[PDB]
Image: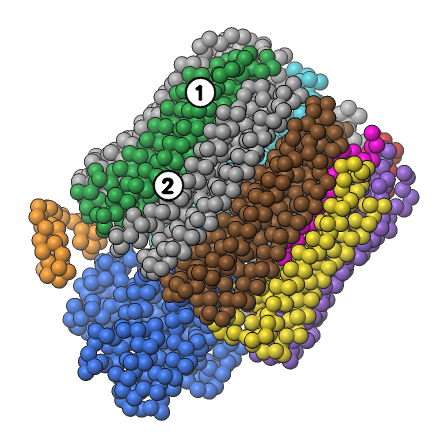
Chain colours: A blue, B yellow, C brown, D purple, E orange, F red, I cyan, J green
């Protein structure tokens, strides 16, 4: 049973992460945030939550939405780092895998800044704290995929995922890295994560893969360099779209073909027939993360909390934008499930 | 002495008692703990007011009641001064194995169904009847085990 | 794996040995009844007592670390929960109390039997009774302690989430504790008519 | 007796126990998997709940097969029965129990998949029922073999 | 640095490093970090700048 | 006796049980996996529901082979039967049961793959049926061996 | 009867069962993996369906090897057969069965790989055929050993 | 003899070994887990070092209980002791050893969790101490049962 | 007889069986891994097909070693053979079978690697041949040991 | 004799082996874990090398305990020793050896953790030393128990 | 006789089999690992094939050690050999076989690493040779132990 | 022959085999792990090869301990040896073998870690040597226990 051996190594971790989940903003707290009309009022209301005095070091006039997002995300990062410092064994590997996606983000960010001739220090300061590795600053030396792989990426945990650069090439490399990483993380969950967390993490990683596959299928239509053979190299092989709808999207050239492929799955129909595609994926991710919190002895709670806080920072940043820019008609367009 | 009542038959009678009660407690605990994980999952999302969420836990406990009943009936027939036959010992071992493993299976089914569906019939009362019916179908497995154990106890004593 | 390889090898050896004994006309040489008759009743009684107390303590400690790790994790943000979540620790302790009480009551039966009455009806009965009642109490207590610890972990989590949610999970904990009580009662009934060794 | 040892009822008692044990395991697996599917599907379409109850009923029928064979073996069990009678009862219990265990696993897996599909495709309900009947007849064949064995348990049997 | 230089130069690395006895304060991290004086040998201008 | 020991019916009863038990396990695996495939595919294409049912029917036929051998062994099963008869009944049961278990594994795997592929390629249905026939004849060979053994079970058998 | 004991037919019956059981297991593995490959490649290339059926036929031939040895051992079985005959029948059954199990494993793996690769390279079909013949010849060696052994079973036997 | 066979001291010697070994394993698990927790905690909060040593000491008391029982059953050992006495010493050693094993495992898990929590929440130190006291009385209970058995070991043995 | 008990041919039959069983298992592993390598590389290099077939041929040679030892042990079998003859036959069968199992594993792994490398590098074919020959000599040593044993199985053996 | 069977020294030799074997296993685990920690931390902090070596030394003292008990048991072994002496030597060997295995586990885990932590927290070293003494006395308790047993090995022991 | 039981050659034959079996297993592991390394590195550096072949050669020499012991033991086998001779032959076979198994595992791992690192560092070749010699002397020590045992197998042996 | 049964040399031969088998296993683990460490290190720093060969040499010394004990036990094996002599030889073999197995595991782990660290920090070399010596003393303790046992194996033994 799940609770029999879980608490030997993860009882404290899971209790702390569930306290973090209790810290997620409820619907009433989001409504109170929405009622704010100034960013100082937003800071005041947000101090009545578990964010607390995270903006106390920021003066009233210096307060910007970018600062609010940066400090909320920093709080997220410190909480994740504390939870990972208490982890050992398979839980430590699980949270390292969680960091591997941010590692891929940092690699793509470094290469994007390098080909754009941005300041090296600025790119390093903008790198995600999660997903940092020691040889990350060395990625500025070259604009060649082979040169960076031999120079840096062969020693990183992203080395298994790689089996001059421009914006489209960096995009392709990043999406290939994501496909390989999602497949590897799915395999790791299948083989090394106990059953309730195994099923929850398989569902969550499959949803993430499906979101990426549908995005790639829909965004390759407006491009000509994305060959149908290249689309196969970008679509992950772990989701509910795999392998049927994944194969259908890897060959589609029109929006109707993509929509017909997505009518295959009962989980994602209506995503393309109404609303915004990204709103559907955000709502589904928050629904899945909310359901993952119904499992008590699952380490998938860490991933669910991480995604819920990322969505929470997105929501708070959107509310900050609909406070700063006026635009109070769109202030309620945030995903909330807690 | 009597060949049909060797002095080691109480070993099998007491093994029946132990199997009955231990396996019934194991099933009851599986059901109670897994259903309670479901109940806690209901918490901080949809905290109710009236406690219909305790039905899986109550039926898990009824499994331990089945095992208790069979174990008590077996232990009533076990005495160091009475002629306990080897047939009676095997009958009591069968009583214990029957009721205990049936209650273990009932507890597994009750735990699964409770964990998954107590949330879903507290969220929407329409599913209450169906989920309770599935839970009754999980409970009757232990009921069958106890019925067979009762018949076996009667046969072994006579 | 290796452990499964040993399980298969032991099963194969047992089947081959049993078939060899059966085919050669010596199936009765594997005499479980004679083994039960000639084995010391003291081994059964002492194994029953030791396994009773030891397994009861194993379940108690098991559930204690489950509940306690969850309580300490949930107390980082909600330190209030500790005082009334100690009830779960107490519920896990009561299991080892059951095991200790049964061990005392059963060890009261551990008198010295006379040499010519070592393997009498009553002495063999007492050995089997103490063995199986000790296993019953100890295993029921191990199961009850694990279950009560799991439920107390969920209770600590729910209490940290909301104060009002603790009482329902506490009722679930009481239902879990009934299992250890029933194991106690059945262990007492199984050894109820077991005389001391004479 | 040579033909009726004192341990002869051991095999019959283990047969009865096996009939209950393995059919209960199969029924529990079938009921659990099917119920998980039912609850996962009724979160959106509650009216289909009483339609998806079918695999749980199939698992219950498997358990009833086990109960029937156990009762029959119980009433065939005796203190002075033949070793052949005990072998027959053990074979009957093993056949019904393990056939019903296989049936229950098939029922759990098929019923889970079928209720998931029927929540999406109303026409797949009849296909689910057909596959479930095919998984049910496995336990039925185990039942039939157990009844035939039990009918031959004490037929021309010398004490 | 030695590992990276080995990989970029595809072997063929003549790298020497010597320990500096005293730690040297760095303003970036405000730490008294130990340092090593290193030398690496290569011919082409492109590999020098890399 | 010597040629007919008291324990001789044990092997026959175990063979009778194992026939149905292992053919039921193979039939259950085949039915469960093929049914998962069918439920997956017939969510979108219910028109293929009764074409895709054939692997389930073939697993059921495996179970029928097991039931046939179990009945035949059961009716040749006696208290004073020979040990040779018991060995032959055990061999017949084991052969049919484990050949049917292997055949059911193949039926489940091939039928799952073939119903999932036939939803995309209608021409793949014939290939599925051909591979399923090749899987079914494994249980058929087991049945043939079991019937030959059973025919030799009480022929030229004395004491 | 000292050298023709009552349990002598046990080994013969076990060998007769083992022949067909293990060749059927090998044939089932070969058929299952080759058929998964066939169904995977015939979605896009249904024209190659009857070419890709070859590994399934090789696995079926493995099962036929096992059936042949089972029939021969069965017809050499007797109530008063020699223990040496039973040992030889057990050896023949194990030979053909486990050799055909290995051959079916090889056939399944190689036939899967070859049906997947032949859809991308038509000239790889002959290579897959050669490797499948090599895999089949393993079960053929097992069958040859079983046939020679079965020939020795009642030769000069008292 | 019947009451004093030659192998009777085996159960006493192996009970002494069990009493020390299982309690030492529990205490070592407790010391290792709590000590890793302490090292992790005291990197950033070295002021809590000697306050966090409590779980390690409460793990050591488990091995001390095992040592007590080992000393007792060792001094009750003898070449010509009764099987009654040897099984009494085996029961004492097994009871204390299994209790100390469980108690030390619980002390390790709870002490690790609690030193980490008290690093984050100083109010959790008292709760952690309380849970560790509850975990330690379990080894105490095993010791008590061992004491009862050892006291009864010398009764009427001839 | 004390020297030639009735169960003495059991060891000989088991040695004859295991000689072919384990060599066929090793040869099957070698064939399977080398064939996967071949069918993975020859999609882009179908010309190298008859060169990459070598590891499959060498695994076949391992199986032939097992067959040779099996027929030699089979023809040395007899109802009244010595227990020593049975021991020697079992040792021969085990030697050739398990050395050939090891050789087949080495052949499969090395042949897979070599076929892939030769698809990547033409000059690596000779090195692959050397390593595969070094894998063959393991099964050949097993053959030699088995033949030397079998040449002594009935050498100075008393009834 | 009855009290001194020929196999009585078997348990003594096993106990003498067990003492050193399991204390060396515990010492090896402690040395390996602590040494991995030491080599990890002393790349950046070579000055802390002879300070972090302490868990390795205490792991070695575990094996010294085992060696002492092995010598003391070895010099009490005899051909005509009593079975009670053999049981006592076995119990002492298992006592010291398994208590030392536990102590070596604790020493390795705590030494690794504290050597790594003390690289970032100099104040953590005294805490590591205290925890490691608490781990070492676990094996020292087993040494005490083994020494008491050995003292009683040939005490009041007859042929 | 009492010192030469009929089952004494069983231990000798098992030792003769185990010598070659386990040295061939170690040689197969060494050959497989080293061959994977060689084929992986020679894709880019074919000129190094005949240098990197060395770990495969050393694994082959492990197998040759096993063959030597098997030949000697086989020629020392006899129907009426002593139980002491059988035990000694079993010990020699086990010692050489398992020492060569350990040596072959070390050779496989070290040769894999050293050929994968020698393709990058030519100077690492001599170091890999040195470590491989140290891994080879393990099988050599096992061979020496087996040879000494075999020399004592028939020395001062009576029936 | 009560004190010297015919199976007494079995334990001596098993001890003689195990002394070299398990010490060669420990030496093989030490050599293999230290060797992958050395190869990874000497890719970058080929000049440090002869410094980094120490863990491999030290594992080899463990194997030499095992060889010494195997030779000493072997030259005390006798057909009419005492059962006590065999038990003592088995104990000596187990002592040295499993102590050196633990020592070689510690040596592999610590030598890998220390070679890799001393690649970066040359001051870590002396510390790695210290930990490696502490891992040697485990095998040395096993050797000492085995030598003492062996010295008592044939002392004051009768028939």
Please state which of residues I123 and F144 is positioned toward the viewer in this rendering: F144
Q: Is residue A91 above or below residue I107?
A: below
**Mark number for residue F16?**
none
Q: Main secondary structure of the magenta part?
A: helix
- Residue at the disc numbered 1: J151
Q: Residue at 49% of width from left, 78% of height from top? A: A268
Q: Earlier in the sequence, mark 2 or mark 1?
A: 2
Q: Residue at 77% of width from left, 56% of height from top? A: B147
Please report, as a chain letter, where disc 1 is located.
J
Which tag is nearer the camera, tag 2 or tag 1?
Answer: 1
Quarter of the N terminus of chain J within the rendering: top right
Q: Position of residue A76 (x, y in %)?
A: 32, 69
Please state which of residues I24 and A337 is positioned toward the viewer in this rendering: A337
Q: Position of residue J12 (x, y in %)?
A: 49, 21
Q: Position of residue I56 (x, y in %)?
A: 48, 46
* Residue A249 appears in the picture as rendered: no
Quadrant housing residue B135: bottom right
Q: Residue at 84% of width from left, 41% of height from top? A: D79
* E23 horizontally vs A22: left or right: left
J77 falls in the magenta region = no
Secondary structure state at the residue bearing disc 2: helix
Q: Is residue F143 above or below residue A265?
A: above
Which region shows up in magenta?
A: B1-28
Tell me if mark 1 has few (under 14), some (14-19) or many (20+) residues whose alpha carbon lies within 10 angstroms of its own: some
């Amino acid at each position: 049973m799940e609770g029999v051996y879980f608490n030997i190594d993860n009882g404290f971790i899971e209790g702390v992460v569930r306290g973090y989940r209790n810290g997620l903003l409820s619907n009433n707290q989001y409504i109170n945030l929405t009622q704010c009309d100034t960013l100082e009022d937003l800071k005041l209301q947000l101090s009545s939550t578990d964010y607390g005095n995270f903006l106390s070091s920021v003066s009233s006039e210096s307060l910007t939405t970018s600062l609010i997002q940066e400090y909320a995300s920093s709080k997220l990062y410190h909480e994740f780092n504390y939870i990972r410092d208490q982890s050992s064994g398979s839980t430590r590997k699980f949270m390292d895998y969680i960091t591997y996606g941010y590692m891929i983000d940092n690699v793509a960010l470094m290469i994007t800044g390098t080909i754009h001739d941005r300041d090296k220090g600025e790119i390093l300061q903008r790198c995600h704290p999660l997903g940092w590795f020691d040889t990350l600053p060395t990625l500025s030396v070259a604009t060649d995929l082979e040169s960076l792989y031999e120079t840096v990426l062969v020693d990183t945990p992203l080395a298994p995922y790689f089996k001059e650069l421009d914006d489209m090439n960096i995009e392709i490399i990043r999406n290939k890295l994501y496909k390989a990483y999602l497949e590897d993380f799915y395999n790791f969950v299948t083989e090394e994560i106990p059953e309730p967390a195994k099923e929850c993490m398989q569902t969550l990683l499959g949803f993430e893969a499906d979101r990426r596959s549908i995005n790639i299928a829909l965004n390759s239509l407006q491009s000509s360099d994305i060959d149908p053979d290249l689309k196969s190299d970008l679509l992950p092989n772990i989701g509910k779209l795999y392998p049927l709808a994944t194969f259908h999207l890897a060959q589609a050239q029109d929006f109707e073909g993509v929509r017909a492929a997505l009518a295959n799955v009962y989980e994602y129909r209506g995503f393309l027939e109404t609303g915004n595609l990204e709103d559907h994926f955000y709502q589904l991710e928050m629904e899945l993360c909310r359901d993952a919190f119904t499992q008590q002895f699952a380490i998938s709670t860490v991933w669910a909390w991480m995604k819920s806080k990322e969505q929470e920072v997105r929501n708070i940043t959107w509310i900050a934008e609909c406070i700063a820019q006026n635009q109070r008609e769109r202030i309620n367009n945030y995903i909330s499930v807690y | 002495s009597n060949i049909y009542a060797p002095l080691y038959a109480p070993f099998f009678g007491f093994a029946g008692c132990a199997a009955a009660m231990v396996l019934s407690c194991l099933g009851a605990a599986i059901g109670t703990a897994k259903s309670g994980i479901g109940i806690a999952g209901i918490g901080t999302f949809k905290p109710e007011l009236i406690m219909k969420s305790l039905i899986p836990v109550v039926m898990s406990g009824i499994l331990a009641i089945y095992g208790l009943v069979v174990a008590v009936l077996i232990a009533g027939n076990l005495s160091p001064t009475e002629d306990y036959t080897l047939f009676n010992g095997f009958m009591h071992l069968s009583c214990g194995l029957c009721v205990g493993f049936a209650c273990l299976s009932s507890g597994y089914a009750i735990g699964m169904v409770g964990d998954v569906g107590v949330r879903k019939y507290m969220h929407q009362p329409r599913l209450f009847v169906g989920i309770v019916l599935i839970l009754i179908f999980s409970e009757v497995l232990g009921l069958y085990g106890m019925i067979v154990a009762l018949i076996l106890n009667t046969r072994g004593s006579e | 794996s290796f452990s499964h390889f040993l399980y298969y090898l032991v099963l194969i050896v047992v089947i081959v040995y049993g078939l060899y004994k059966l085919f050669t006309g010596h199936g009765s040489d594997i005499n479980f009844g004679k083994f039960l008759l000639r084995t010391s009743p003291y081994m059964w009684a002492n194994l029953g007592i030791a396994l009773c107390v030891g397994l009861s303590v194993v379940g108690a400690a098991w559930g204690i670390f489950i509940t306690g790790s969850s309580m300490i994790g949930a107390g980082v943000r909600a330190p209030r929960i500790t005082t009334k979540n100690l009830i779960s620790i107490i519920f896990c302790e009561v299991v080892a109390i059951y095991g200790l009480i049964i061990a005392i009551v059963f060890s009261s039966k551990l008198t010295v039997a006379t040499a010519e009455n070592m393997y009498s009806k009553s002495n063999l009965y007492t050995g089997y009774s103490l063995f199986w009642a000790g296993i019953t109490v100890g295993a029921s207590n191990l199961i009850c302690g694990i279950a009560v610890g799991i439920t107390g972990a969920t209770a600590a989590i729910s209490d940290a989430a909301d104060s009002a949610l603790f009482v329902k999970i506490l009722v679930i904990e009481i239902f879990g504790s009934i299992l250890g009580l029933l194991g106690l009662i059945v262990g007492l009934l199984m050894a109820g008519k077991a005389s001391e060794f004479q | 007796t040579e033909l009726c040892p004192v341990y002869a009822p051991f095999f019959g008692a283990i047969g009865c126990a096996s009939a209950i044990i393995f059919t209960s395991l199969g029924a529990a697996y079938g009921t659990a998997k099917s119920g998980v599917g039912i609850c996962a599907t009724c979160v959106l379409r509650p009216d289909l709940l009483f339609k998806n109850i079918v695999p749980v009923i199939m698992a219950g029928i498997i358990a009833i097969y086990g109960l029937v064979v156990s009762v029959l073996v119980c009433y065939s069990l005796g203190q002075k029965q033949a070793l052949y009678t005990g072998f027959i009862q053990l074979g009957a219990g093993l056949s019904v129990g393990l056939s019903g265990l296989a049936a229950g696993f098939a029922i759990g897996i098929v019923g889970d998949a079928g209720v998931r599909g029927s929540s999406q495709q109303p026409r797949l309900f009849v296909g689910m029922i057909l596959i479930l009947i095919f998984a049910e007849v496995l336990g039925l064949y185990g039942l039939i073999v157990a009844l035939l064995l039990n009918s031959r348990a004490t037929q021309d049997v010398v004490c | 640095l030695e590992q990276i230089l080995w990989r970029v130069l595809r072997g063929n690395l003549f790298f020497k490093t010597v320990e500096i006895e005293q730690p040297v304060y760095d303003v970036k991290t405000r730490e008294y970090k130990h340092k090593n004086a290193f030398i690496v040998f290569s011919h082409g201008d492109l590999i020098i700048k890399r």
